[PDB]
Image (cartoon, coloured by chain):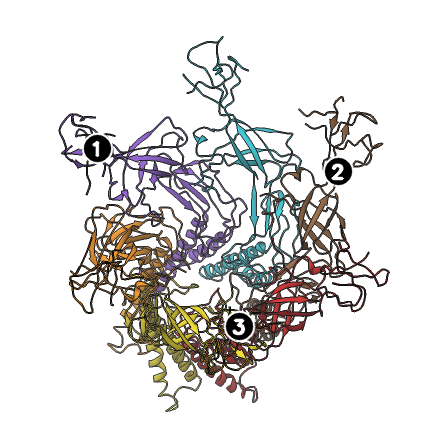
Chain colours: A red, B yellow, C orange, D purple, E brown, F cyan
Amino acid sequence: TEEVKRGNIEKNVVATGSIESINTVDVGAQVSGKITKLYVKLGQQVKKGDLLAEIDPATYEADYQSAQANLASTQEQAQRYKLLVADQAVSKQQYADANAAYLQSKAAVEQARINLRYTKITSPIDGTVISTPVSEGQTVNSNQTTPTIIKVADLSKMRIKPEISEGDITKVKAGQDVTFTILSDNKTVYHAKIDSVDPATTTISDSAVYYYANIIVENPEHVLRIGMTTENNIKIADVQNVLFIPNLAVQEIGVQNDFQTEVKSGLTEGEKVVIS
Amino acid sequence: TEEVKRGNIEKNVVATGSIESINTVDVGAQVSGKITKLYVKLGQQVKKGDLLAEIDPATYEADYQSAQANLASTQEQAQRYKLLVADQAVSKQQYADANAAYLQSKAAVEQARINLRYTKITSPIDGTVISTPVSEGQTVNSNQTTPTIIKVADLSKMRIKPEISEGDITKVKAGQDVTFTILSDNKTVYHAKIDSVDPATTTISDAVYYYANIIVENPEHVLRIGMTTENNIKIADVQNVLFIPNLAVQQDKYVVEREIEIGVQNDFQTEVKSGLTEGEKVVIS
Amino acid sequence: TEEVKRGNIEKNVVATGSIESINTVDVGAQVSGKITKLYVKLGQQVKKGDLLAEIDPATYEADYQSAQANLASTQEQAQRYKLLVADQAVSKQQYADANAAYLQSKAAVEQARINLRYTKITSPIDGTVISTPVSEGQTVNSNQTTPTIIKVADLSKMRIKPEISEGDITKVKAGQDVTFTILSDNKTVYHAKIDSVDPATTTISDSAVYYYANIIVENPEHVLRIGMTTENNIKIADVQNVLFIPNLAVQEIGVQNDFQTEVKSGLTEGEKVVIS
Amino acid sequence: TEEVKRGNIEKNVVATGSIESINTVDVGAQVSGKITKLYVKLGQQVKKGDLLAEIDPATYEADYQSAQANLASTQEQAQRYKLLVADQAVSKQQYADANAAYLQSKAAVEQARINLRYTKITSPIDGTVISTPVSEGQTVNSNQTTPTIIKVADLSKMRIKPEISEGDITKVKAGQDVTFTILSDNKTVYHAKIDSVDPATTTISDAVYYYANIIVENPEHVLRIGMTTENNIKIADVQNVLFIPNLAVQQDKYVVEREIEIGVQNDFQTEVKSGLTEGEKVVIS
Amino acid sequence: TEEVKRGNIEKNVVATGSIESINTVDVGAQVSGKITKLYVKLGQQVKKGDLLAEIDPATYEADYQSAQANLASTQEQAQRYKLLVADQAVSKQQYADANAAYLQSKAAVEQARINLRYTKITSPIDGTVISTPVSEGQTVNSNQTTPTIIKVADLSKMRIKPEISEGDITKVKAGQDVTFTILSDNKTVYHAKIDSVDPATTTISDAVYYYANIIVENPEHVLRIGMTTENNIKIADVQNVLFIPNLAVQQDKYVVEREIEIGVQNDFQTEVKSGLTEGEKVVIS
Amino acid sequence: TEEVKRGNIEKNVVATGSIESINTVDVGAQVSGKITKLYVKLGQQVKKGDLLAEIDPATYEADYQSAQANLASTQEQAQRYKLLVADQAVSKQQYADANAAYLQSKAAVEQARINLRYTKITSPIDGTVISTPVSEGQTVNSNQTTPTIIKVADLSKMRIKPEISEGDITKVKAGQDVTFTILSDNKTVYHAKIDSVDPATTTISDSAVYYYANIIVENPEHVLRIGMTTENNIKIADVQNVLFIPNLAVQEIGVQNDFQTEVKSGLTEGEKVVIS
């Protein structure tokens, strides 16, 4: 039920997208020691650096006392020899060692002040709380296994990850128009564009070889989510306006797709089919 | 095979809930060294901070002696120079170092006093004892793998985790009325509401699912915790529009006729949009 | 071949018990360093704290010399200034520092004396030796992986663990009479009582959901053992003395069991069946 | 089809024995650092403590120099004040500190001398070399994973481990006569006795089994170690009662007749209790 | 069915190539502590040493203050005693210790300056960014598990890894002409040469295979890296001897006749040794 | 088609050999810290100790400065008191402490000189490079997981590992003549002898029980390789010259092999068969 010409070729490829958030981060600090006060739940919206947080801060407060006293000393000291030499009382060598003990005891102050700034947790981006692995009583411990402790990420702006593959990868470039949809609200179709390839076999990012090729786009509302899978198709050609042979020239010039080719050379219209 | 005056549907979805306790925590300390005295058996009711607990406290008592002597010294010292300068005997610089040794030896006292407060265990909430992995003779050790040592949690108030999924997730919101029940006492049905979604694929909390927790108070023992439940969740309720027992079945198209508009159904007992008035030519079979 | 009344209902449930010892502990110390002398085998009866034991004690003896000399010093010292001031010879500040070096050198003595008490092993209960993972030549090492080194536990008093399940758990309470038996001596049947539930899905203690419910009881002789599995049944009801309808009232009032119900309301006797 | 005067049964059980060496040990030291000289190849006969061995000893020789100088000092010192006071020159308090520095610097000498004695390897028993996991160039390292480095064990005297099981375990005791054989030399049969049970499910030492070891001297090479054996174990022996080739087969009940009493059999050649006298009407088929 | 004058064969073998980049490296430093500023996204072209990078540098700046003061001191000091002795004021032994404190405090300055140079990341080659495992908030930590943190490598010049195997390995040497192609652009065929064997079972680099790498310049993006290729490798080429389309098929024996001598074939189009002259009685079918 | 006598029995056993190199070693040092310069590729021939190597040597050069200055000091010092006492100027106790600081500062010199000798890598045998796991940029790190970093071994002299088994192990001794071949060049057959058993179930070296029994032999050229598998057969008997009954004496005296026995007692020749 077909004949000649037009210009509606759409070549497409299709793979299936695992969808994602644009960023996304796990958080637990260089400290050890059990925790005390936990500030969030499930899926809170959180703006920058917040309160999460807090391992018991106890011995770090200790070490603050100890380096702030031994700083009050050296401070008074070289503040006093800051007024000798300025007469010419004692030396220019007794100044070097009063400054040394000062600077050294200020350093060692900003140090254990840091290890207190550790004990306080902070969210590394304004975002939303995915996970909360970790609990008010929880005797965490670092050393060599960072813990994480809160997971959080950004869900306006999401980005989908089309497990595309080894064959069709000489094509799929950037900026190709794509459409895709879910599995959750079939009457929709989302369009976007394709935004970047990888150049990385998605084993190699984070038998059976895929090459992601991310597409981003803003989720307003909270509609989408994150684990989700999508079905997606990606125009790898578009000639508006040449010549179309509903398929079979089988038992010249391309390309064929899907089974519905495409006349370039020469020719022109008017013509035939195959039947049968 | 007519109307329903105007009528009343329940769309529901259903998934299967792994049930849970509201909170729940594992406990074992920053210390190492073997233990000595263990205070609970599973399924003890425990109120706050209690006695669990206790790794052998031996070398931590040592370090208490050693920092409390070296504190008795500096305390006497700068308590003595606290009465010089207040004459004007010795200086204002020999005070700085008597205070330094004091503060420093008080600090290092609160430190090893802390590492004794570690050795003593405490329960991070008033609750009940799930597990007791760990035993009177047991030569535990921290460093880099925290142990836990007691698990304990709260079982009045429980919360169930309906492994719901990728399809139906555009719906299920919060505050939806839900009912569910177990596998253990079939003549029951518990109602509750739905209390929160996640926004998190339940791999990503802790084949694609998205939990959506529902809480509610367990009085008595009754429920438990490992349990699974079967649960169904009203994703619509129109009290009072028009009901076509299903088929006008398809660019959807709808036999007797006219055509209609549509939606929605469930379990296969579709709903009208115009339609259609009352009585009409009812379409079957 | 049946009619009315009585009072022999036994509802029962049944699951299969993995049997156990009441306690049970693994043992290897905070030390490192290879071992030397090992005192037990296979399944010895052992009473408290014994000799197991002993990593090579060598450098810990070293550190005993070193802190016991530096203690002989301070001891002589402040024993000598314990007799000044008691005249009024030297000061009250030279006493503080002689006591300090004393206390400090006694502390540091009880410390490396402890690290020698480590090197000696001890059994944390009068019991019996399950396992002996670990051998006269064996270059063990702690740090962050405790070793264990002997396993030992108590086998008078055993306790069985009936993998019971998600359905029948609204019933099975405590104090229910139970019977169970093995797989090794079929002409027996052991009775006991049920002694505690858990409230813990036996994944959660130490697809497919079970809830243990321990039952203890004394193994005299050594007959039972430990790995064993048992088959067990647990009276979750007993009405002595109401009304019994050999089953089928199918195509009122309960409960039914197994297929052999149970008349409450109203009624009385004399009556029928089903046939057919 | 009569009696057996009085007769002689063997009940047996049978399981399959994984065979073993009596002892057996893995060896690699508290040290780190690469190695240098390796003294054995597998299947060397070795007698006690030998030369294995040797991680590069380099920095441990360093720490020997450094603690042996600082010992030469304190030795000369308090050897000198060992001749004051014995006049009455200098004090009784300057002796305390010369002794302290002495003892302390002898201690710290026996310490780094020890960490040299580590660097040298030694075989924890006179025996034979199973394995040699570890090589002349091999940059080993301890800390928290002890290495092993040579495995060695004793192969005169071996001991076989009959994966026996949950049923038959109420029987099999110690001192039962056993026979077993391999898979490698079928015309043999080795007898021994059974020497110990366990009381330990062979998951729990190191589908339910309970080992029950049997030892015996391997002279020559002959046996080996990975081997499996097939073994059978007399759990009864009545020399001299009455034997009914099996069936009176069932509340057990026993055809010709009369009835009997019973037990026991094996492999299906049952035994009488009364019974039954001599000759009788033999029941078959 | 005759001769080939003298004729021209291609034996080939074939295996399937996993393709690769020439180099390729993972990068994350000796430091610990969380990060702060991250400079790249995957698939950035990067030239040498760049900005990646940066764990929070905080306490390393601290230790810079502390060792640069204690250096200002000793510098002034021995700069002052650099002008004694050059009179002859104080000694030649008070110089030794002023130099010692100097050198020692310069050393400990280059040390903590180093641990700041750590905190800054750098790309170990001019190349392109594969991976970016690691994120602006990410609380990394070293010690004993190096992290990596960026992966990057070189994609002009790629090299393909033909999982070739245990049989054909006595052949395939180096410098053999090869052709191969993908799975993604079938109208192509890439030729190259073979550039090296391994001598290493490709389990042992990083069912038995032996890689045998072939390199060649990827200009443009075109290829990629995960890819598989299908590749065939001329293990013989006699231009110009005699060709018997196969069968004289067997102590091998060769119908029409006479007999021949033989080899070799492929895919089943065998070759003569005498044979046989021209024309002859061609054997079929 | 057979009769009596001779002396061509060959009993043989057969198993399949995984072949190997005689030695073989993995190499990466006690250091940490990233690397810098890497000297080899794929399969280089390398003679002893070479250049491989080199983690960035930076802070180890630091610690060389620091202990070589503090050595220049003590060296000058006790070189100066080496000329007192030799008059009789200052004491015999001030010498002890000048020597102490000297020896101690020489020790501490050979120490950080060692930690520089670490940073330089060296091949633990003249051989060939199997593997090169590890790369110019590679931020390696030891502590508790040695890295390895180059793998290298010897491929003249190879040694094959005949997964032989639990049955036939009462036989296979040493010095038995063996032949074997590959899978890669069928027209060959290599002979060798058998050179050692193990006494070790090849799980136990480095359901289903094998016992290796190595055979070595020189690979000249580079022909063999290493991953390879071989098929091998091993004469466990050879009587040249007794009496041979093509098999079946079935429905005396052995042994039988394969199905082609072997007359000892008594007898003599001339005789029969089985047919049928």
Q: Is residue A163 above or below residue E276?
A: below
Q: Where is residue D22 in the image (x, y as percent from the top left)?
A: 35, 39
The residue shown at (53%, 15%) is F2
Q: Say which residue label 1 marks.
A: D237
Amino acid type of the residue tagged 1 in the rendering = Asp
> What chain does badge 3 belong to?
B
Amino acid type of the residue tagged 3 in the rendering = Val
- Measured in 3D between alpha carbons, the distance from the residue under mark 2 to the one under mark 3, in whole angstroms, is 78 Å
User: Mark 3 and mark 1, same subunit?
Assistant: no
Q: Residues within 10 Å of mark 1 (few under 14, many from 20)?
A: few
The residue shown at (64%, 29%) is F188
Q: Are marks 2 and 1 in contact (CB under 8 Å)?
A: no
Left or right of E104 on screen, residue A267: right
Q: Where is residue F135 in the image (x, y as percent from the top left)?
A: 63, 56
- Measured in 3D between alpha carbons, the distance from the residue under mark 2 to the one under mark 1, in whole angstroms, is 76 Å
Which secondary structure, mark 3? loop
Residue B283's disc is: 3
For the question of whether residue E238 can be seen, the reply is: yes
Left or right of C98 on screen, residue A217: right
Instruction: Give the label, 2 or 1, closer to the camera.
Output: 1
Amino acid type of the residue tagged 2 in the rendering = Ala
Q: In this view, does B156 lie above or below D50?
A: below
Q: How crowded is mark 2: few (under 14 residues within 10 Å), some or many (20 or more)?
A: some
Q: Say which residue label 2 marks.
A: E236
Left or right of C69 on screen, residue F191: right
The residue shown at (40%, 30%) is D222
> What chain does badge 2 belong to?
E
Q: Do the residues labelled 2 and 3 touch (CB within 8 Å)?
A: no
